[PDB]
Length: 444
Image: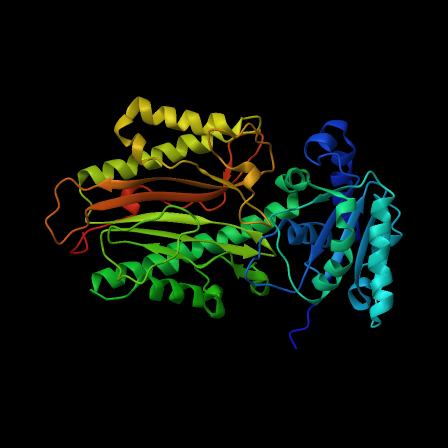
């Protein structure tokens, strides 16, 4: 029931494994990003739809094309060992004698005998001892279950024999540069996001406000989210989505909706239970296509006043300059500082209101934290990277409000972009001029 077809792509597995190995075997990277490990240990437990974003599961998606629950990988420079169930293992078997192999492929099959299975785990420990005993791990990852429990039973008592180190960033560097298929996936996701936004959301939003509909943000948000189960919606032709495999579509997160003078410009914002107010309305939404993430976010103004329109137009102008700065060879922290600098030159008054970062990288993971766009990031943008770019202003105080009105507002723009050898590609682009996103009572 709902049994899928899996095409394990042996070519892409070795291409990508080799990218990883080349960097690990680089003296610099090996010392810096991989912290001088001789092995990388990666485990994935039972499926947990509670954290969809992990280095561990991203590794799976990147190497194998899919997440394999309850499996263990031990990467070595000369060999990759994957320990899984017989049925999963048989799928991976084709990786083991490809002519274009990047490494030895060592597949260990879990059976139905506890003791044998234990012997398999014990092999892993033995491989590690034969090394410098520095083991690369992804420390922020968390997993759980039966498989994991067995592994712990075996590893934890012998674990002090080893030196566990963070090789997180060596993977990050690999994942950061997207190939042609990956970019395609992210563009697809982006296309769905912006279509839902431009078409479903703005429609709902505008009629609600118009028709004085009393709806909570959470209600509305949940309404949006439930849209995914309505495939009729995605076949709407005006949505030029005809080429999207709807069965490979998911939400990145629960859409964030905000109004009525209470805002949170962090992607971790949870949509409250307060009623939608027709003043300044923020929306963030993103889809995940074939396991690649996207994000879009927009501001809508209802009967905005002059200073509100001015601030919103300045944000648009700022984001434009942001795109322009996002080019191959640019230092990330310079980009932030240059934007801050534009504020101080033209709208210094706005500086206390300015976001502390401008988002981060995006791909398999919703957030590639190595590519956090803040002042301190010394990393350099390269062609083929993808960014989930966020820019905005918070706690903007309304000067003169009659008391049927919100004291404060915020402004936000998010788009997903690809770094090129020139100007970036803004996959999630849509008209965002004040006139596009402004509504005036009486239908103006």
